[PDB]
Image 1: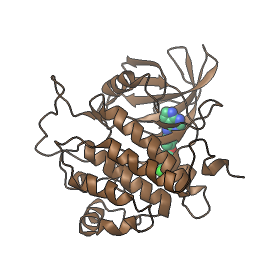
Image 2 (image 1 turned 45 degrees about the vertical axis):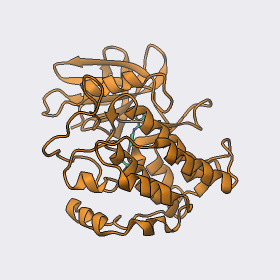
Image 3 (image 1 turned 120 degrees about the vertical axis):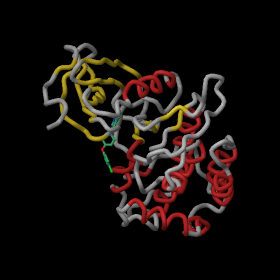
Amino acid sequence: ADILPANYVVKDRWKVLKKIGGGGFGEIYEAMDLLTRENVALKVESAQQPKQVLKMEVAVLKKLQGKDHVCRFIGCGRNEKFNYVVMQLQGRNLADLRRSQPRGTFTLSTTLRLGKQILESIEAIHSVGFLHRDIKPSNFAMGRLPSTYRKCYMLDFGLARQYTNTTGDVRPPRNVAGFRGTVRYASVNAHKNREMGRHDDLWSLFYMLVEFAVGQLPWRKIKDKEQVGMIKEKYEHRMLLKHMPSEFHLFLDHIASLDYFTKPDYQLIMSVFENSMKERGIAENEAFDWEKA
Ligand SMILES: Clc1ccc(Oc2ccc(Nc3ncnc4[nH]ccc34)cc2)cc1
C-alpha cells in the first residue's frame, strides 16, 4: 500500500495524480494544485514511522529559497496520519537521463556543465550549515519549464543533517553514524560508518562525474554494501581519472586531503570544471546532450 491513493486531495488543495518514487524514507507524488492549476511535487511520510525526517527537510528547503538549483517551496503540513511538503515539480532526473544516452555516457561538454551546476548546489546547501549525504544522479533533475530546462536542481533533502552548531562552527562528530544512503556513490568514510562531512558530498560528486563521463564505475555490479566498501578503499582512484580531463587530478587530490573538520576549497573544484571547458572550448549556453537531435 502507498501512503496516498490516487485522487487523494491533501488539505483540499493538492490532488494526487500518481506516485513518482522516490525519497527520502518517504514517498513522492506528482499532484495537481487545484488552487494554482499547476502540477506540483508532493512528498509525504507516514506519521507512524520511527525516522521522521520531514520536519528539518522543510527547514533546509526553506533556508535555501532564493538560491539556484532549489525547488520553490509551495507548502507543508502535518496531520495524525502523515506529514507532507509541496514544492515545484521538475523534469527528468539525471540517472534516467543518462541511461537514455546510447553508451550510458554523456559527453564531457554535458558532464562538465552539470558538474558546475551540481557543485553550486552542494556549496549552497553547505553554506547554510547542512550536509546532503545522499548526492546521487537520481537526486538531480532538469527543469520542465521554458525558463528552467537548462537549470539543474537538487531534489530531496531527506538524508540531510546540520553539521554546524549554535555559533555555526562545525559540531563535534558522533561516535558512529549509521549509513543509510545510496551505496554506489558513498565516500570511503560513509562506508566505514564514520560521521560524514562537507568533503564526503564532494566524493559523491566526484564518483558521479566519472559515471557521467565513462558510463560506469568499477564497483557498479556489487549490490552488497561492505564489498563495495572494500573495493573502494583498496582501489587506486588515480585510475578513475584516466578518461576525465587531466585537470581532474587536482579535484581528486583536494578531496583526498580533506577531512570532517576542514572546509573544502570549492573555488578550486570550480576552476577544474571551468578550465576544463575553456581548454575544450565549451560555451555556457551550448545544448545539453538530451536536446541533441
Ligand atoms: Cl535509480 C532511480 C531511482 C528513482 C527514480 O525515480 C525518481 C522519482 C522522483 C524523483 N524526484 C523528483 N522528480 C521530479 N521532480 C521533482 N521535484 C521534487 C522532487 C522531484 C527522483 C527520482 C528514478 C531512478
